[PDB]
Amino acid sequence: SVITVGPYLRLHQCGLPKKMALELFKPFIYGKLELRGLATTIKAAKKMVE
Amino acid sequence: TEFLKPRLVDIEQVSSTHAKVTLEPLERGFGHTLGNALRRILLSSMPGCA
Amino acid sequence: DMNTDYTLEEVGKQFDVTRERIRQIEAKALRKLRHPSRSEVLRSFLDD
Amino acid sequence: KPLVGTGMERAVAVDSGVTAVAKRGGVVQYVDASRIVIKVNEDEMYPGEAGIDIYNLTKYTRSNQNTCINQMPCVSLGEPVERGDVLADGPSTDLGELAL
Amino acid sequence: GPEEITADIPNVGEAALSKLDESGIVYIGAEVTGGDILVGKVTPKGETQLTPEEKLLRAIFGEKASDVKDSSLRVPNGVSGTVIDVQVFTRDGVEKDKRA
Amino acid sequence: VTEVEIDGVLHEYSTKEGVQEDILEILLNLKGLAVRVQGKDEVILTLNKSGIGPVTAADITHDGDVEIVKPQHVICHLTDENASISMRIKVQRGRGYVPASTRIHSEEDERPIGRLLVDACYSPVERIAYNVEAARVEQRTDLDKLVIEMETNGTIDPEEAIRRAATILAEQLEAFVDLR
Amino acid sequence: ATILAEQLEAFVD
Amino acid sequence: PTLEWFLSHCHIHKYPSKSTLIHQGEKAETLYYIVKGSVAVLIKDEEGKEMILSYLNQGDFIGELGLFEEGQERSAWVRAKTACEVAEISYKKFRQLIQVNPDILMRLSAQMARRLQVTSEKVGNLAFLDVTGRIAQTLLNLAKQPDAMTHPDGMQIKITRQEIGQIVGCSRETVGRILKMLEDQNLISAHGKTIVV
Amino acid sequence: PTLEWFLSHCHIHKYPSKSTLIHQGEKAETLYYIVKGSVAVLIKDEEGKEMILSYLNQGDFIGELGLFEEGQERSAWVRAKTACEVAEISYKKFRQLIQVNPDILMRLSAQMARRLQVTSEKVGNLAFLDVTGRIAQTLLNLAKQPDAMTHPDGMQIKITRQEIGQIVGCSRETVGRILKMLEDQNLISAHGKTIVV
Amino acid sequence: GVLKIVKVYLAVKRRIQPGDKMAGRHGNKGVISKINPIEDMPYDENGTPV
Ligand SMILES: Nc1ncnc2c1ncn2[C@@H]1O[C@@H]2COP(=O)(O)O[C@H]2[C@H]1O
Ligand SMILES: Nc1ncnc2c1ncn2[C@@H]1O[C@@H]2COP(=O)(O)O[C@H]2[C@H]1O
């Protein structure tokens, strides 16, 4: 992505448009939804994502 | 009208005099309003003996 | 579970005879499973 | 527009060919959100021809680089017109002068 | 055989169909977003087979099918906008499907 | 205004016969509009009109329980005489600039065609300043007087707003006195 | 904050 | 004519046989109209047999039941005996068009009157007639059902002692024997075909 | 409301209890409406044996299926079990009133939907249940219809056996028998009134 | 092999956000890192802010 500044930030921190991490952290979430069982399996997980 | 307010979240108290305040939530555009008028009156209106 | 797909006549020639009452068993099994208590682990594969 | 100029900018806005001009001075007959019609002056009019133009305009359309296109009048109707003048400004144009 | 287009699609939510004509095509004025359908196109399909597990699935819900495939147009992922204008081109020799 | 809708049109990018403007230019002639609704947080007004010449607020269908602030917030111009216009204009009450893009984002309630969403800037205020002159008491000349200059739309009483300032400031000040 | 409320006793009115 | 007007708003989805179109308990969101074909209603004994409430032909609507009210789920299973085309429109669309158009409610409510009327007829034939009387009532009333091959002495239909049962309600062998009995009264004739002599 | 504007030009009668308004076979000529009270709608077979198919309360229309088609015989006996205020509307002017105002038909058709639902349940549980289950569905639904008192933890009802004999249309002696057989099960406690735990 | 063709156009609009690049007439590039509520904007004697 294009970039910019966080003047407030500290060292370890970094701005992140969230969709990026969102789609990039999907199977974490799918294991996690099967774990919660809101999405008992993964079709419904993606549905509920939508 | 659909106002918001903050709740005093904590008084993290180091000492009797040296002390913190957490405070939230606010609508945006006020933390500086507050801090401005707060510190103005505190700096520019207080009685005492000397 | 197998590389096979066993079918009708052989069963009689293997098990004993029967063919039609198998069908009848089949339908009644659809009864006891279909009733929306076990049909839901499929019901989103209905959407497959 | 901008506000500081150099002077050329009028002379630029024309020979893009990006919008109509007054081929022949006249008066506006008809106006539309898409088009216009004029009456040509007699002296400019030639005998066999009726001497009226139409100008049908460029609405929302694309480039190679695929951005909007549109044209529209800077004028009113039932009013005189001198020749060579403009009819309609463009996506970045104003009174025959660029506006980006 | 010849491919074809019409509203008829299998395994549909009428949500998408709500905006498509009898020829299976969007009406103007609408707004759309990624994953919506634009035209229902389909292609003559052959036939195949499946695993015993999906067989077990289709065997109790009674899942039934046809011999044709979907090849329908959709909005790309991440995109949305307003429905304003279109066109169709058809052979001199091919029947111009009604709305053409 | 938060929405408008009209006869004869689908989408903003369309056009019309007998008109100078586009749709949206006229929408922008409307964003600069003022209303003083009395009882209601939302209405629809209506309009119908025909005949060559400008179309202003004078032409519209006013209901008596709302004060219009201008007759001549200019809107459009009829170029041709046979043209006619007929629209309805939904106004709400609110504050700020969550301009109904927020609504469609929040609301995929399946609307019909025609309903022109419009951006909302409920905020009435336009300009403001203050000056710290010296509130005269014969002794306490360190006292200060504040003169606040203001500019807004119509729709607004000054002392209404002032006492509302007092109201909400004190409401929050509760949390500074009462809740500790 | 109390004293500010005391500043504003004029104008809740 | 009014039908084609209705269909002008529809999506015709086509369904081969066995297409279990509706499942009872599905929510009701969609109206159906038979464009082409005929279809079977079905209700299941909660563990065992399901029974055919009736058969339906061209000209009529399906899923009308849930319309007037929210949270209305589907009443019965609905399976494609034959391959069929069904027209698809929704609710409020439909409510709007009823504001626009009359005569659908006329025809369909009169047909509901026939529905409840013949349901009374079947409740009566259930209560009063012994089973031979029931089967014989069926033998009459289906010769006049428009599916009857003209036979110069009687009416001929290709029932195989199966749907006579589902409509009457009985085991199949005893239907064999009471046909074997109506074989003896010069009323009926058969080869798996059937003729009402 | 709309109600009174309808009624103000209707020939109001007060019909006391048991009065046979309608003898079916009569040729339908006038629409009625229960302004107040309660009525039973019922039929017979030619040997005399008769069945109640419904009762209708204030808020309900009857003579409603004859209105549309001109000159067909009436459909069932309709006899006021109570002192009932009835409106009376000849069909020829009621059709004028429909031309003057629609939205009179959604509600009749909704309740015909309800009627055919429950009648389908009648025919089903007929096919299904030994009388035990039939009494089961009965005492359930009568503990659900809006005349059931509560016994603090339990639906009280007292709509006594003479009446339920006619509701299910069956011998009350077996009703008492199975009711005793359900008091064995303790789900019911019944003496004149039945209390459903 | 081609039998008839359809084509369509939608319309899309775009509005301003950080990361969107910006400049004038001197090489004077720049990118947005923030957009300011008008209150905390500095401003003049006449309140007419920047
Ligand atoms: N007794 C009956 N006779 C004829 N048709 C019926 C009967 N019961 C139900 N149906 C139809 O079967 C359908 C099943 O569910 P629907 O809600 O779609 O609407 C129902 C009616 O159209
Ligand atoms: N099986 C039934 N269950 C409930 N009510 C019925 C039944 N059959 C007929 N009715 C009622 O009896 C009425 C007789 O005349 P209608 O056909 O006008 O309308 C009929 C319904 O109101």
Image (cartoon, coloured by chain):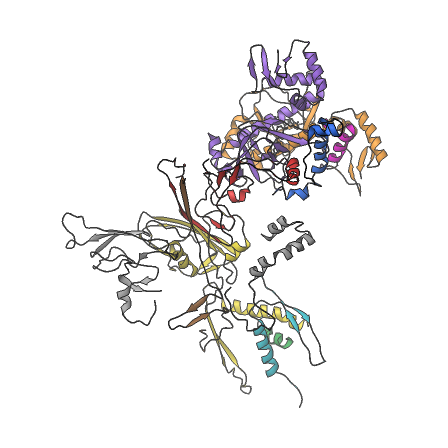
Chain colours: B cyan, C blue, E red, F yellow, G green, H purple, I orange, J brown
Asked if residue J4 lies left or right of residue H60, the reply is: left
Magenta extent: I127-146
Asked whether, in this view, residue D45 is left or right of residue B29, the answer is: left
Please name whichever residue, H5 or E80, is drawn nearer the observer in this view of the structure. Answer: E80
Q: Reply yes or no: does residue I142 show up in magenta.
A: yes
Name the quadrant containing residue H194. Answer: top right
- Rendered view: I56 above or below B25: above
Q: How many marks?
A: 0
Magenta stretch prevailing secondary structure: helix
Q: Residue at 65% x, 30% y: name it.
A: H42
Q: Position of residue J42 (x, y in %)?
A: 48, 75
Tell me which image quadrant ligand 1 sits in: top right
Residue situated in front as seen by the camera: J14 or F51: J14
Residue E17, x across and y down, in percent: 51, 42
Q: Nearer the viewer, residue F19 or F123?
A: F19
Q: Position of residue F173 (x, y in %)?
A: 62, 71
Query: Residue H33, relative to residue E18: is it above or below?
Result: above
- Placement of H151 over or under F117, stated as above or below: above
Is I109 included in the stretch rendered in magenta? no
Residue E10 horizontal/vertical position (percent): 54, 39
Does residue E4 show up?
A: yes
